[PDB]
Every structure is written in C-alpha cells, then in structure tokens.
Amino acid sequence: HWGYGKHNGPEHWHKDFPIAKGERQSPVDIDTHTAKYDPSLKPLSVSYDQATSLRILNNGHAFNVEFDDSQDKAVLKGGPLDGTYRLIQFHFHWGSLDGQGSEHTVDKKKYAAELHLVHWNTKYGDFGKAVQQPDGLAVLGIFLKVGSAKPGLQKVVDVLDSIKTKGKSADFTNFDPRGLLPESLDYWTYPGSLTTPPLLECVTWIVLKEPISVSSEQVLKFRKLNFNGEGEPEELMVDNWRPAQPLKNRQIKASFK
Ligand SMILES: NS(=O)(=O)c1ccc(-c2cn(-c3cccc4ccccc34)nn2)s1
Ligand code: NA
Ligand SMILES: [Zn+2]
Image (cartoon, rainbow, N blue to C red):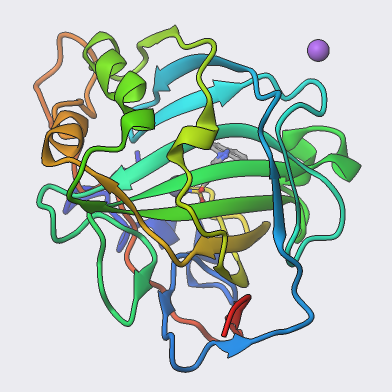
C-alpha cells in the first residue's frame, strides 16, 4: 500500500491512482509574483463558534481531528466559494527537519508544516458524495513556521502520546479550531485535488498568506508519532508531504494586493 517511503511514496502513487498525473493536482508552488489580485474575490467567512470536535485518530499517515458534520455547525463560506462548506476534519503534514514539511510552497519556500482544515459542500449531502464532485471540497491551508509556541495547538500536542500508532484514537471533545488561525485571512486560491490517494480532483484550495508560529517542541512532538501499528517495527511519522505538482492550465488568484 501507499505511503511516503522510497518504495511506496509519491513517485509511485500514479500506478494505483493514474489521476496523480492529471490536470488539477495538488499541492503546487505559489509564485507570488504571478498570482493575480482578483478584486472580485470575497473575504472568507470562517464560522467556527459552534464547532463540535469529537475524536483524534492516527490513520497511519497523519492524525485527524474529527468534527460532528451532521449539522451546520462550523462552516466556511465566501471567498471563491459558492455555497456552504461544513468542517469535517483537520490534519497536518510535516517534515523530519524544520526546513521541510509543507505541501504547498511559496516562491519555492518550504515551511515546517501545513494545516489542512477540510470542508465539504453541503449541496452534495455527505462527504462521500462531495468528494466525487469538482466543487465538492474546500480545504483551508495554513503554513506553520517554527518560532514561538501556538497556545491553541498545545491540546493537540498533548494528546499525541495516546495515539502513537496507526489505528489508535482518543476522545477529543471541546477543541476550538479558532485557536489555530493566523490574524489575517488574506489568501491565494486555485482549483486542485486531495494530496493523498485517491488524489480526487474535487478541492477548491484556499491557502492563507500568513503562517502561524509553533515552537520547536510542538513540532518535535509531531515527529514522535508512528506510521506503523502497535507491535510493528517503529517508523517515525515524518515527511508525510507530497511535493509540488505541475500547475498546468491553472491560475492562482490573490485576495489581496
Ligand atoms: N491533504 S488534503 O487536505 O488534500 C485531504 C483532505 C481530505 C482527504 C481525504 C482522503 N480521503 C480518502 C481516503 C481513503 C479512501 C478514500 C476513498 C474515496 C474518497 C476519499 C478517500 N477522504 N478524505 S485528503
Ligand atoms: Na446530528
Ligand atoms: Zn492534507
């Protein structure tokens, strides 16, 4: 099966998932000089006041913090989007070293990590349906640099010891994802895909310009997770990012000048 190793990593994925070589793959490099300001874009609307977190799961390639998406509770709207998108989960991608780990890059700069807040378009009724549609998902991507600690991340960091290995989960109620956002909601947007198999071309990407800062100790703790299951040889969960893919016939739009 697929993963992030020499023998099953991103260069291999196309054998099982040929859309790996498709026309709207993610992530991409964001060339800031070529992205055009689009004054027709709206401010984003991030409405997380009623978000209801449930659980945190090590799924063997990241950890997902899962939300109750059975009603409109935590929704993303505006920006480039038509309609209402419901938060289902967030996760991260990160490196073995502070100088790598993001999936998107900015003028070829790699950040230490990247947060993905995953939302599905309510007009399609459920996530499973939405992922089959070109406008099914909206993923809010936020870069992480290493510097000062992010206080709102610490509850995440503290639970990781209890989900060390693939298949483990833990209660994760009453977590407020507002505490992971930067000050500014300035963003880039473009049409793309899931960054993990099955690589479905269903995502409107919204990538915030302002990174959040986390401490070296917070990211060190991410790197103590395991890709393996319990009782199996230990494989540290690091460098779980896909590299930048060809832009092809796409424009990246800026919400700001
Ligand atoms: N990294 S990402 O934000 O692009 C992302 C957000 C959501 C993803 C995802 C992958 N999924 C799947 C996993 C395994 C099998 C699946 C089969 C069909 C559809 C999605 C599948 N479901 N959501 S990947
Ligand atoms: Na419900
Ligand atoms: Zn992701």
